[PDB]
Length: 271
Ligand SMILES: [Fe+3]
Image 1 (tube, helix red, strand yellow):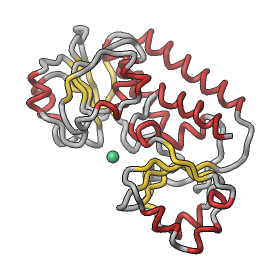
Image 2 (tube, helix red, strand yellow):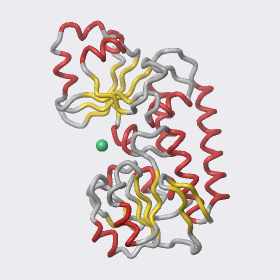
Image 3 (cartoon, protein in one colour):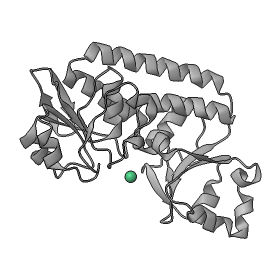
Image 4 (cartoon, helix red, strand yellow):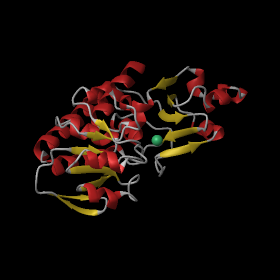
């Protein structure tokens, strides 16, 4: 078995039994083929993984924050496969390799397609190419079926908000790619190149999505401070009251197949 990860070639002979994953998308790929990771970087909060995944798999031991995992906690779990993020864990990758063979894959800031590609590479590295390939095809057809239930040209835009500000998830974000797969139009330019866009109130006005779905990280947030602005009423999502609060765990953090399906289900209930 061999894959190309974000550093080149990853090879494995034995079937890994104890897997430690450092992101939530990887928890999806393992759960899709009934593999329970023994360790997850869950930022010390298992509820950040959506319940549809944790129902498929055994409970895990937390190895700490996704941005800064505990190498000790990982090593104590005695894993034989570590699945890390290409963006978040470039610096600690070589330290992760000291513990066990480490696969460097993308999730944060990468497309819905690239997250599907990483699930395929995970299926190879664990020895379930055929089962993972079949699970991915059943997902692609499920979304193609949801693409028929939707018949609207309204623009939908997701973003996370906090006291710090608002970040619009562009078409090349995971949530943006999920919407494109469902045939939903995006209000942002087709050539937007960053997934999480720092969004000023003026930028929000220039975009003016018909639907603004927002995952709240802090109550209250910068959006409430923008409602103080009387210019806020010019927003289509404000006019039609189509500014809806959604789960940031589902739409931003989890970035998996089973979350894309719940997104298509949740998007259906809105329309
Ligand atoms: Fe984050």
